[PDB]
Amino acid sequence: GSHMGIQETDPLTQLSLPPGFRFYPTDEELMVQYLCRKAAGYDFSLQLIAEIDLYKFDPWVLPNKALFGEKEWYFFSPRDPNRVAGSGYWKATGTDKIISTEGQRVGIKKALVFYIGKAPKGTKTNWIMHEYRLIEPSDDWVLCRIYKKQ
Amino acid sequence: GSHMGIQETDPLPPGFRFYPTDEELMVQYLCRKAAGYDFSLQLIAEIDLYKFDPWVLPNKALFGEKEWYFFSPRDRPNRVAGSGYWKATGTDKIISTEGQRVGIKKALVFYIGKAPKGTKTNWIMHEYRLIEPSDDWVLCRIYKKQ
Image 1: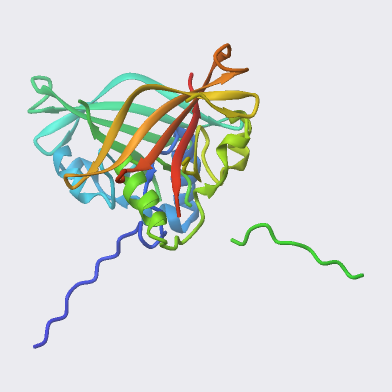
Image 2: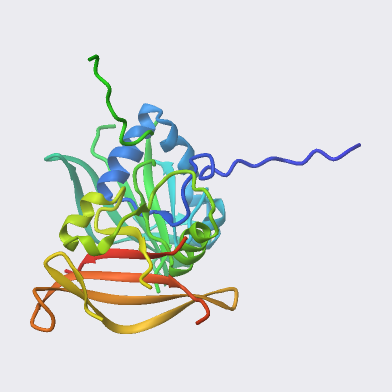
């Protein structure tokens, strides 16, 4: 019959961002305003970062699965060494950092790098992940920044 | 007499900050204002920048943690402001959009005292202006180096 298109919801234009505004959150904002608030059901935290299983994908596919982003993308992924994803694996690298708010430790930031192939014979790529997790015992997510170096 | 007050202003998720490109500042801010367009909110306030010491300017700006933006009247060398003067520095850049030149960006630095015997400070201004032939504003970024 007559055509009925699908109307997709741009989650930024609902917020009416003036031009020039970009999402450059501090580590403390990602923990307190996004990760902690997601558990609390806060609107902007639910609607601005996509729930996704990161380990089902090759990282170069991920930019298209993010609700927004130009050189960095953010996701919530289910909280769980060389863990497999797509045609490769993510390897922990560098030094884990503790994130604090108002003198309380709230989160840990972990860096990882994507290798293509099968551990431990894979080759390093420029895809980086920053996995932010809450300090809390055993719904349950980590917050991840994905980007490509260089 | 019952009390009659005055309402100064009338009413962002976390992590959102103002990081405009040179092209956005020219097209989306300066050009729109020159064209007499309305804005959803006042973000970049009108001010006479040359009435002030740069270190009080963060207080007059509606937003910004380390950079502040203003619209200031377009002037029709070492121009005086407060206890000092702004000196042009570096290389003026041309801003283009879709292959058209639309603006010039000019860097300046604040010196305290009386020209030409002042002392350099870390206060920087970037003055963006519309290109034109030989409602009149410049748009200025203010920040402190280091």
